[PDB]
Image (cartoon, rainbow over all chains, first blue to last red; front, side):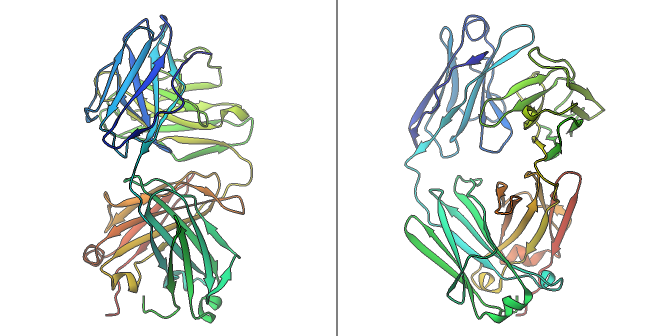
Length: 216
Length: 216
């Protein structure tokens, strides 16, 4: 194979603390003291938090600290934050210039406060209306947990043609941001009296409306 | 870290040669010659495929070869295989406590025709400004492969803070859609001349600007 063993998952609670194991052999983890850990957020480059077993680089916080016993290396993340929620990989030297990587470890931070979303309807731009198009956008942001459902309505009558909805995605503050768009003709933008973007998060429903009347 | 810039998406069909670039910003980059390449299949851990610019680690075939220009490093996959599909990162320097990783290139084996994105930038609506809110939206649509890089500039200067970008979500027509929003103050919004959203995708770069208007 050549892969270090790490628990598939490890939950904690804000202000709580975690400990992720990483087990190798006497050839790799047990052989040298070149055990480093990687923090990778869904969709980003990996970031080195630990290197050389228990050495924290430039900027890594202090609630990240690692240690090694025999064949297993471990990383303690205390006073869990919201942003510690990522995938954590461990890796070890194994000679001949080579590196072996651990399976990943996904750490989930429990008890994060709920936040209903902030919806934002944007009528078609002048610019795009000038090219003969009209797409309306529904920006749904700062919501937690991360699951919404959106619906469109032209004049309180429902719309299923040509609506495209994005999957939530964590922001700089571990809240989600999704966006639904509805594309149409400069001609339909105009014929309806209203278009609203309806959004349900955790049972509360927020619904915004935009009219082909504005000055914007 | 002195950022390592990597194109967003890189593609071809089976049998073609795909080169990825890696351009440092500093004194060679992150600072010099110890640039390695990692391949991250989907959902698994990183893997070292090239180290010390063009050395191959062993269990690593011949089709991967590495080189370095001045400030630019290049990985080349020749006669692309289905299994070559994954994310690809560059990294620079062990020497220290700061090991910077590149931005990641996403190798795709063309499952359909390539589609440069459709960028649509929207100014903050009349309502939302009437609310002391100011939010720009930049809709990116119908692109394939599904990886793009978004930059924002306020009066030619790149906007640092307040930008959130989504994750390319498959649409119903099988192409992707993404979006970033800049969060401002009627204050900030109104103070600049023009605001720009630039999106890169596979050697195609679009850029759209909006200017504060008013009415009132």
